Image 1 (cartoon, protein in one colour):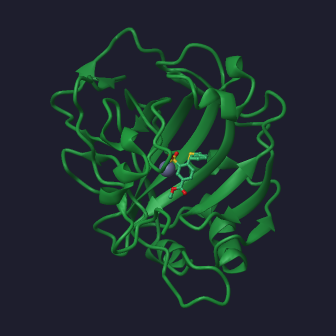
Image 2 (cartoon, rainbow, N blue to C red; image 1 turned 180 degrees about the vertical axis):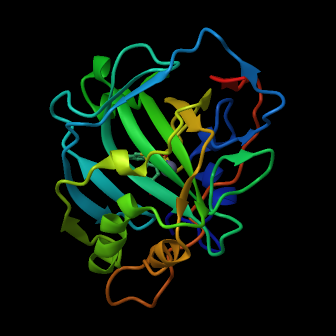
Image 3 (cartoon, rainbow, N blue to C red; image 1 turned 135 degrees about the vertical axis):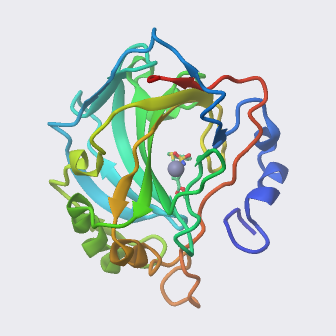
Length: 258
Ligand SMILES: COC(=O)c1ccc(SCc2ccccc2)c(S(N)(=O)=O)c1
Ligand SMILES: [Zn+2]
């Protein structure tokens, strides 16, 4: 009886195994755009993905991870609200059963069709496992997806999904360039929070871009053909793998823009 997003093991149950679920800096949150404070001290975000080396794509049972070689300083996030240098380890998405839901963060209560998370760890902690034990261990860049025109830079991901339909399947996935998933503007909101799946560790500086990217109805439909179940089990479509907004508590969301 492990955690998931099904009818009996979903987000409202997670606190029983992971009491940090009811903690002081949980994610995601609703971003109240009127209450977010412009912070002129924030720097432009620096996203340096020119030498990113993707390796593999994995159906992890909850979403799919596109994994990067993070054994050298290649693909890094810095600047913005961050001190030092964070290295890209993987990206994944969260999405809905319908276009009107699927994002984890919300903007003035608006839910997007999906949300991309590029996960990076702080190089001062040496590796990902040590970084997640620290309050400034991770930086996750969050990008909203809306349904409209296709994103040509997403198609290589969508095309490989039929090869990893079920939990625990992986496929080689080299030479994928995550710069093709970025919107034009790097204006962002930022706040201190958590992983959004167990173990829900409070180790993330969230950086959520204001401008969504557009993907086509066909691209998102292919996400919804994935399965939460293993091969040779009855089909459980991989949809609605998003955690809802959590209480903001004693936190301020800062904006990089006025
Ligand atoms: C459906 O979502 C996922 O499948 C998923 C998978 C990994 C991660 S971050 C890496 C990680 C490693 C080990 C344990 C937890 C998280 C996240 S998130 N939203 O917290 O960034 C979400
Ligand atoms: Zn995520």
